[PDB]
Image (tube, rainbow, N blue to C red):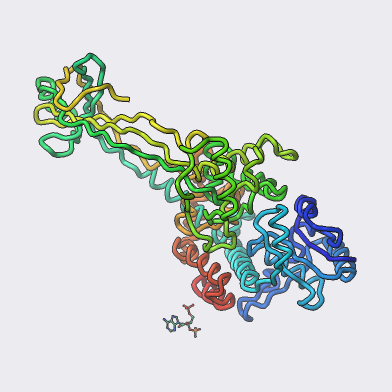
Amino acid sequence: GKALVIVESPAKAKTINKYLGSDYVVKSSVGHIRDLPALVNRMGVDPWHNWEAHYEVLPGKEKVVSELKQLAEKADHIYLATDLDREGEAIAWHLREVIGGDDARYSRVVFNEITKNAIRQAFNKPGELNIDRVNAQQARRFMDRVVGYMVSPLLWKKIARGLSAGRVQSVAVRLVVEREREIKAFVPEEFWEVDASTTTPSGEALALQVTHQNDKPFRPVNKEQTQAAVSLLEKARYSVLEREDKPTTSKPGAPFITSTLQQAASTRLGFGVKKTMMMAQRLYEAGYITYMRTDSTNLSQDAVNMVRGYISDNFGKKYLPESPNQYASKENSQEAHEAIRPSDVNVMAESLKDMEADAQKLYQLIWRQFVACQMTPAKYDSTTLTVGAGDFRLKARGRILRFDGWTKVMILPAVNKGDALTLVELTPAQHFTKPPARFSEASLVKELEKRGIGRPSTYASIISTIQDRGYVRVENRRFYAEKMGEIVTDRLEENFRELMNYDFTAQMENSLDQVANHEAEWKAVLDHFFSDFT
Ligand SMILES: Nc1ncnc2c1ncn2[C@@H]1O[C@H](COP(=O)(O)O)[C@@H](OP(=O)(O)O)[C@H]1O
């Protein structure tokens, strides 16, 4: 009968409750409490009557709503403590609209971390439900509903029952299909490379690749031109034309954001996209990391000071940059203002108490990326040898690590300019250009991000769905378009070319953000969407 705080999961309720006093009753409403269900009747949304929607409490959740009602009235003030993004904003909105009461009866608290300071400042300066966000979510919802209920039927008719088209997953399948057709159509190009094994004045071995002939790039295309070059190279005199020594540096990557976390988690840990977000959310809800749906590589000042503090103690001076390493500002298309990082750098992956082995591995990846992004660059001594042999130009590259810098948390022989090199053996080799590489789970996420097709909340879903529906399959960690995906794609491009257009999809995603950021109105965006779509 004090103050009621609503969160979306038991796990989140147990953690936030640690930072809320006696006058706070924390209750969770597992996921979506309310949602969408002739053609308009089934969709639960009317594109022909200014997007009139018909929401209804989820099947069976009729109890939860009541448990909340008689608990809310029994409450002083109601705090909507859902995740910070527009999705959590709509869940908050649905809760307020179902429990009822006056608006001044609710507050929307915002935090991107479940810690003592974060929850304090969140309940200290509570805000109001942001209607633009809610409308952005609704608009995305209505767009997906319209596409699915109006396109899936054509797939049932022209191909098979059980098939379903998605506004974004459809374009994602096209990306894999095109790549499949690009690969099958690829015609290998023959080309040769000549290498030269040589000896330094002191004896040390040195391998060189022929790069230029008569000051033009060396690219023989057949056995005949190669044999000619080899014959000249056999009788030429080899001498070092140049030894370029330059200090090179390697900078650490930026702290993670949703897409980069999925890419690295897949490549470095073999974790599937859905698994990463599941472990990530587990970590976030237990208060170990910052919100996991973000496209901001920005880091708060406190987090930066703390990890720099950690870097001094555990690595020393030479690893601590002069000034902090900045990557991006807090402003981005999405709601999250910070990157994915640990809530406390002092907490190692090995100390997490209620986490499975995989959630620990992920935290470990998140932790190391975060600490490394504030460490100094790795320093290398690069060596480029340019060798002359008659009319030919040869080169050899070398590199030796001087300072590991950030890599701590994760060679050519000697010869001077003018030195003579003894030709030991020439190795002419025939090769064939390779087809475009196939998509990996990591390169597909990157592709989706690069084209503006995906968002932090859809990357995973988009990649999981297309595999489940059977349009693509993964084999040996690489993506293969399935015949069914190719067939659905061609039919979709015939009947709905606009839907299958990359720029259309990316525009709609941008338009959604615009609604969220008060730069566009949702019904107008939906009107333009439905208009392009039909
Ligand atoms: N550059 C422009 N200047 C003025 N009107 C435009 C316009 N582009 C589109 N419209 C109009 O805006 C409405 C929505 O179209 P669209 O979705 O393509 O933007 C259309 O009219 P109606 O609403 O009367 O049909 C269309 O003719």
Residue at the image point whose x is 33% and y is 30% from the top: 399
Q: Position of residue 259 (x, y in %)?
A: 53, 50
Residue at the image point whose x is 19% and y is 16% from the top: 201
- 82 and 67: which one is in front? 82
Q: Quadrant of residue 382?
A: top left
Q: Is residue 21 left or right of residue 490?
A: right
Number of marks in picture? 0
Quadrant containing the N terminus is bottom right
Q: Position of residue 223 (x, y in %)?
A: 18, 28
Q: Is residue 525 left or right of residue 221?
A: right
Residue at the image point whose x is 70% and y is 36% from the top: 351
Residue at the image point whose x is 50% and y is 64% from the top: 499
Examine the rendering and report whether any part of residue 193 can be seen: no
Q: Position of residue 105 (x, y in %)?
A: 79, 74
- Seen in the picture, residue 238 relative to 13 is either above or below; the reply is above
- 357 and 298: which one is in front? 298
Q: Quadrant of residue 97?
A: bottom right
Q: Position of residue 214 (x, y in %)?
A: 10, 36
- Seen in the picture, residue 159 relative to 191 is either above or below; the reply is below
Examine the rendering and report whether any part of residue 530 can be seen: yes
Q: Is residue 80 left or right of residue 361?
A: right
What residue occupies the far top of the structure in this picture? 203
- Seen in the picture, residue 67 relative to 53 is either above or below; the reply is above
- 61 and 217: which one is in front? 217
Q: Quadrant of residue 366?
A: top right
Q: Is residue 431 left or right of residue 295?
A: left
